[PDB]
Length: 213
Length: 284
Figure: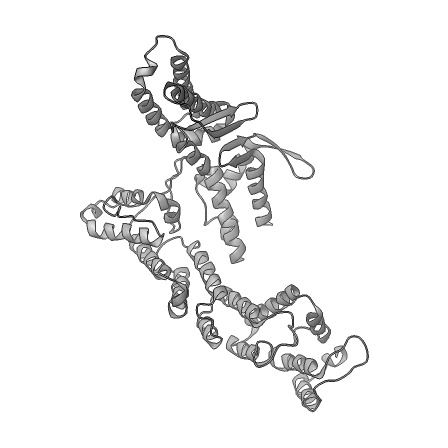
């Protein structure tokens, strides 16, 4: 039953609130799970699963839910599952990577359906100022998915993790591309980049992060 | 059989009836569809008198006529229990070599399962029995050196104990078990370990080493610092190794003077997790 319910949460996460493929990520805060389609809200759901299974956010391999378990095989089964929950959900590793090796790479574009709550990654072949606008729009879409696409704790974790990289990479990009951006006084590029800056500031704020500012 | 089960001096009656049966021919035709040959009945009585009487004769005929997985269920249950309530399991293993786990002929009870399954099972049990000498006693009584399934379950309980490790002390019972399993590997799966056994034993080495230091490498973005160090963390940190030694220097103020040791530590952690080093040894 331990395995059963934890696997249950596992497939709830991987097939419900989240679907993460190698070029897209959709989140939904609400899921109708099971043959009776009972309603579940992502927020308090993973709130309580975290409190229960991840005291102080870390894997509690000495806890009751693991320490009391007896059958060795199943024990490590459920161990690996809770580890995978931690990584993919308590840490969101796959998407973090996806982001980092996606953000500010030429040839990689990212769309965001806020209505679909889907950050889609894709290949691009635009050049120069066009691919600059493209990657700025893509990063801005990533920030859109941060703000309007994530939960408070989700956004918080993901900011905590990449906002340093966000800051430095977006900064250095703007710097290296200072020529084309300040080429014009009023441009959808400058408008958009000021949007991204304000949005990143609001990200620091809403996320309430201190490890990076 | 059900009637003469509940009698007195039962062992003597079993010896008597078995002495009677010993004169019986190879085959025997019996009354109707439920048919048991004299060799089948003989193996049944042999398992009764020598190995166990837990299952009824009808239960025995069932298991013979049951499904393979069901037979393995029954065998697993049976041995699992007998091991708990025998005085010296070795006796029971000999009994298994004698009636059920004999190769000199096929088993007429567990006609649905091979020796290998049964051995695998009693092995896992033995492990749950934390019984080790028997493991290797077995493996070379039946010559499973570098055998797949035994190696696998070894690795399995290995990673199990490893994932049970809260600290890194040699004197730890869990790590004692792990050391003994690795000894099993060393003695018997030499052809089935490549260098990996090396990685495991340097793993234990580095674990004992760090067990003489203080480490709080636990990236808790809610700020949890009340954390001891579990070995498997390194697997997690597989891609951020020097962060480990960094926290070490962060938390062990004199280890900075100890370039060669720390160096060997990185090297061992690398080699343990098969961390590629494409001449970047200079880098790291």
